Image 1 (cartoon, rainbow, N blue to C red):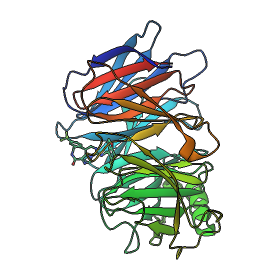
Image 2: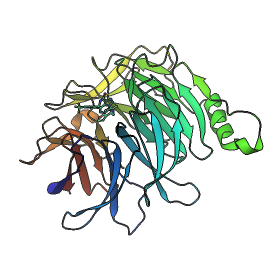
Image 3: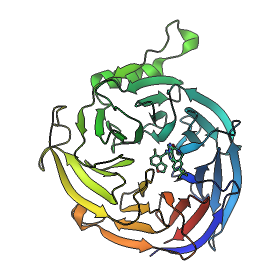
Image 4: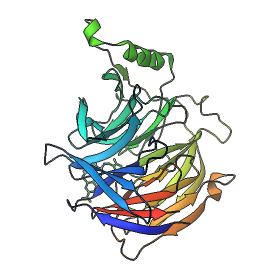
Length: 359
Ligand SMILES: O=C1NCc2cc(C(F)(F)F)ccc2-c2cnc(NCc3c(F)ccc4occc34)n3cnc1c23
């Protein structure tokens, strides 16, 4: 069971909107996590007796930048960890976490970036979701924009979240238009676009790299939630998603026995497999997280309470809930992060505080 072993507060006193453990940290090295809030990203190291050691920050040159998301990857040639951050300026920054130098940046989105995700099998493929209603897929090895997921049949309002499935064959995205949309990236067109992005070297050719314009999702529903959908994650072939209605819904496209890879774009049905209710989390912009193995699910609420669900059960509706409270933790928990082994759970808050829970 989890016990709160420590807490701290960042000096900017602004909300912390993101937190991620580095699940690519090397064997024998202490566990490391990043936080994003105000116009900065900060790294910490977890030590014994609940110690959280402060390392170093990246502070944006723009005092008006607001980072909203961060994601870890590694350099595909050296294995060294890399950290990607983005927010209100709509600029993706690739940071060397050792020195906190910005090694490169990507511009493209017409507005703020709400979430970054790396492909589960390819460390170079980065997905960004934006307030400009689109998703973008980048190849950070050749610095190319592989594809833009948008158009009339794409999202009709700001995109808040997206997630890759287990093999990175498809993406589920969600946002302010109340919809959840599926985008297959294992199509002949998308597998070819990814192969071409790797073959692109602007020093060895005259052509610009041509980005795919994907204007039609492979599935779409507005039947799960009745407000902004601000967080989505795959749970095998099933989906976990939430709005600001005090619930995480577990669902799938089509009928109960329909295989996800047989689903057609015209599919009009969904199946609800369960719903995890909770309290006082009815404000926009609150994220839930799962651990590496997807044995657990965590979400914080707007008054500092943590909910943890044990997903190691036969069916999703049988998940077992644990609640974690501390008399000094009373600010909204925007995001949580589990260490790769789930031995540590970190919660980050609206008052710039960080809470460490050890198993
Ligand atoms: O218009 C905004 N303004 C900054 C802001 C301000 C507050 C306030 F309460 F502090 F005022 C709360 C949330 C946000 C915020 C927080 N987070 C995002 N995007 C990232 C995000 C999502 F896109 C979806 C769920 C999330 O859970 C926590 C962060 C998060 N925002 C995008 N635009 C805004 C946000």
